[PDB]
Image 1 (tube, rainbow, N blue to C red):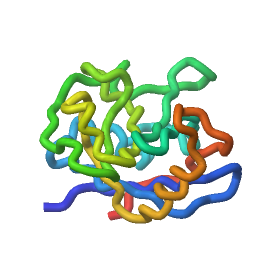
Image 2 (cartoon, rainbow, N blue to C red; image 1 turned 90 degrees about the vertical axis):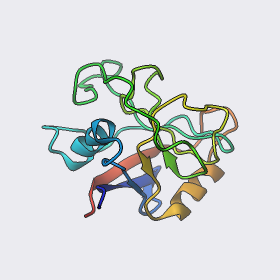
Image 3 (tube, one colour; image 1 turned 90 degrees about the horizontal axis):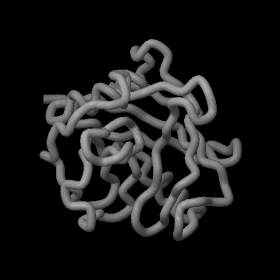
Image 4 (cartoon, rainbow, N blue to C red; image 1 turned 60 degrees about the vertical axis):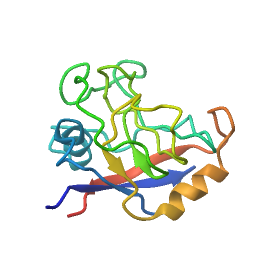
Length: 165
């Protein structure tokens, strides 16, 4: 079979780091993947090519993007507040793993966190539905510009994103 893939042009203060995609196992997590996909693809109806990153922990994991009604013109998980617990067929077995961190329990939303290291401490604490497709070098660069707490000096944002296949 074949799963959908989407890229995410990671920028740093205006300077694009390069290319960073993730292989979303829509086959195992279509309900969760369809979300990040429908958005990145734009089929969602509007999406949001930009987002913002201000929580990168070099040693545990990073952050994705959130938007609803904190700054304005927010959105959602292309299905209301969020969905329900789907499954964990893909347990964090190493770095470059994608998941959801919108809240945890029945809250896949779209607040993933680039797993920069097998997060076993979580143990089925979320829902995994992706994995660094290509350009891992980019994920390694960000870890260098991250603080051991969350915040960071540089501003990481998404310039462009869409389906690859």
